[PDB]
Length: 325
Ligand SMILES: [Co+2]
Ligand SMILES: [Co+2]
Image (cartoon, rainbow, N blue to C red):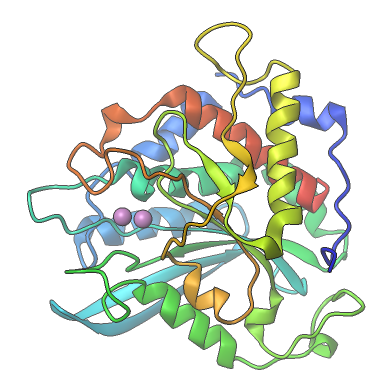
């Protein structure tokens, strides 16, 4: 079965534009510095990070929803709030980009989770801001497609990871959207042969970012279902390299982050409760995990800025191609 939306390759003019960041650099870093703090569930800093996300997106004229709830954990009842921002609420279909904004409660001390997921959080916001003008124009087309950003709360386990202790915000949102009924007749411009019964059917594909910011990540297609989408990430990365737009240590080297193969690895993450509801998932998470994973060294200084800027180019080009910006 083919992808429901025909995927038009990015014009060279646009590819080249999406590929040269330039002194934007300071803009991404200023964004990122807001997330480079402990973001423990329930805490003042966490609440502050959420406020910053909400305000940043409201200021861009996005519809922003705070999906708050209380849930039982091994540490007692906790408050959780997912942030859901939608460029054009009326559009039937959403390209959904996601990450989690809570940070792990680490036994040894204060944990920043710079790759996990402060970087992905900042990348989402940076995409919204850097592509704002083109996004605002796309929104007026009436073509039934929009961009949606989801910052999940409570992804991390409080104690040992288990079905009950983890993914609090994603489990909640998936169930809520699954039970919120709707149909094609109430929505703007759904695709011809699409079946819409509830809100979760409007997620055309969910692209989940996690554990990004370390040097030389390796990605694979984790889902046969979304291979047509994943392959565009492979093609975009290749075109950027052909154009010499990737930052590399020496001349005549290429990035190969997006491997053209698939792997037999199963990663439990915020995608799962959606995967059970037939949401196509692209899971942008390295394999193997960065060495700093869930250690106190997952910190600001261990981020690899050239890798981050290369990933930023790929994601901007990707969103531009999918939404035909
Ligand atoms: Co983690
Ligand atoms: Co994580």
